[PDB]
Length: 154
Ligand SMILES: Nc1nc2ncccc2[nH]1
Image (cartoon, rainbow, N blue to C red; front, side):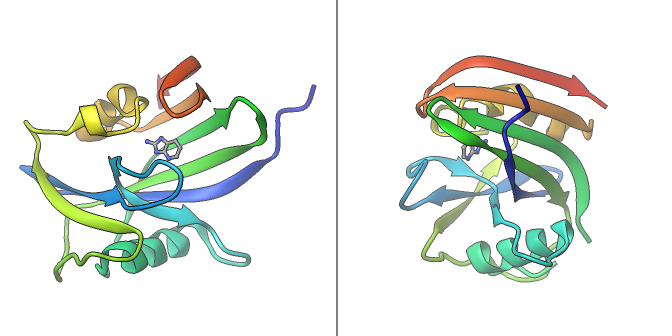
């Protein structure tokens, strides 16, 4: 039948030559995992404006964003998909702050904390680091198990 309906999300990676800024999600779904900053796009908002807003709300940073990929997530037992538009920037001009949602830390690019990131990151995060654009899809059973995935460079 028809592909499930999807909700629009953004995800922003602050990626400098030697390090990346990640946030530890403090509560809710996926709490305890490190990742980029993002959330739901709001009604009438452009995707890039939503990405800037989520970066500011979750990390305090105000920034040019570059579109780097799109990843669709499906969870067993939930008919609605997450359609995540991924962005990255190298240029910041303020300091990240802990928010209600996220605790920030910088990681060197030889210390990407995959053990404490979502399992899908092993597949697409390396493409982001190589500046290669991508489209991916991941079906999860719960928070740990991937039952199916597709990934391509574009
Ligand atoms: N990398 C990544 N972030 C996620 N957030 C929520 C669900 C699945 C996710 N995979």
